[PDB]
Image 1 (tube, rainbow, N blue to C red):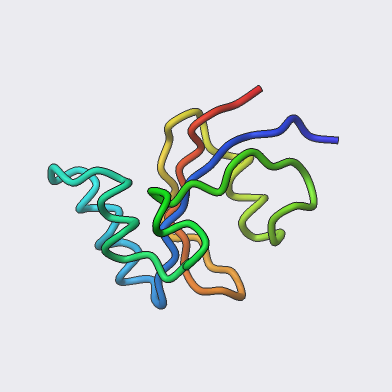
Image 2 (image 1 turned 45 degrees about the horizontal axis):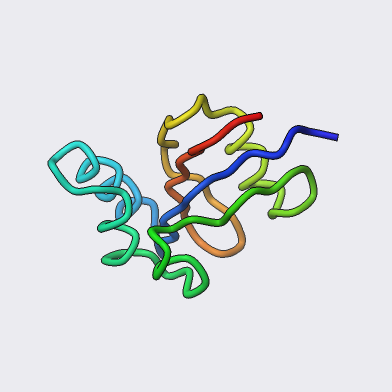
Length: 94
């Protein structure tokens, strides 16, 4: 029912590592570079963390809820899911 959004993410094993990734994004490193260096998501770490376009019910609830609260280009605080901790960036909104 929701409009499709496009997002990238960096998946890490713990919250301290997620806060560190978030801080490094403001220290001169790009999201695409940090995804290659830190992300545990094999399917997106080779694509700058891009997950492509998705709508409601495509991603796990914890990820979907956090992503739909972000403004365009906004980077989330650490988001816990069953896969670990995510740093999410919404790159496009309907």
